[PDB]
Length: 48
Length: 97
Length: 49
Ligand SMILES: CCCCCCCCCCCCCCCCCC(=O)OC[C@H](COP(=O)(O)OCCN)OC(=O)CCCCCCCCCCCCCCCCC
Image 1 (cartoon, rainbow over the protein chains, first blue to last red):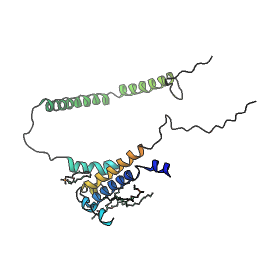
Image 2 (tube, protein in one colour; image 1 turned 90 degrees about the horizontal axis):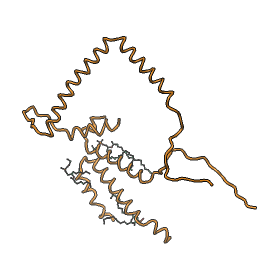
Image 3 (cartoon, chains in turn yellow, cyan, green; image 1 turned 120 degrees about the vertical axis):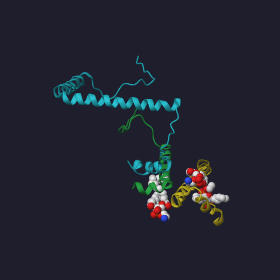
Image 4 (cartoon, helix red, strand yellow; image 1 turned 90 degrees about the vertical axis):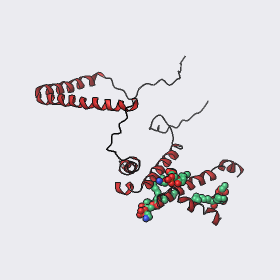
C-alpha cells in the first residue's frame, strides 16, 4: 500500500480540479453567464 | 462543418461591429496598403475575365491545350519510379565484418 | 441550428471549450509511433548445446 500511495499521490487534487472546472462550465451553459455559476459553487462547504 | 454551423455564427454575432456610413477613412501606412491591394486585385479580375473570354471564343485552341496537358501528364507519370516508402536517414549506421 | 447558438453565445463557447479540453487531455495519453501499422507477432526459441 505504501508504494500504491506514492503512485496515487497528486491524482485526487488534479481530479477534483477538473471536476470543478466542468461544473463551472456546465452551470455557465445553463444560466448563460460567466458570473452566476459562482453563487452555486459557493455552496460546497455547507454540506461538508 | 459543425463548428461553422454553431461556433462561428455566434462568434460573428458577438464579435463583429456594425458598419458606419461615414467619412472615416484614415490615411495610414497600415491602412493604405489595403486600399492599393484592393484596387490592384479589382483590375486583375478584369484581366482574368478578358482572358476567359478569349479562351471561350477560341474553341480549337482550348481543346488542343487541354489535350496536350493530359498527354504531358501521362508521359510524366511513367518517368517517376515507384517505391513503397522513402529512405530516411535515421542517424545510425551498422557495419558488418 | 445556427439560430440557437446565435442567441446563446456562452453556450457555444462552453461547447468549444469542452471539446478543446477533451482533446488536450487525449493528447497527453496517446501513443506515438512513426507508422500506424503494428508489426505481427514473432516468437523465438533459443537452445544451446
Ligand atoms: C472530457 C469531457 C467529456 C467530453 C465529451 C465530448 C463532448 C460532448 C459534447 C459536449 C457536452 C457539453 C455538456 C454541456 C451541458 C449543458 C447543460 C445545460 O445546461 O444545457 C441546458 C440545455 C437546455 O437548454 P434550454 O432548453 O434552453 O433551457 C434553459 C433554461 N430555459 O440542455 C440541452 O439542450 C441538452 C444538452 C445535452 C444534455 C446532455 C445530458 C448529459 C447526459 C450525460 C450522460 C452520459 C454520461 C457518460 C458517463 C461516462 C461514464 C464512464
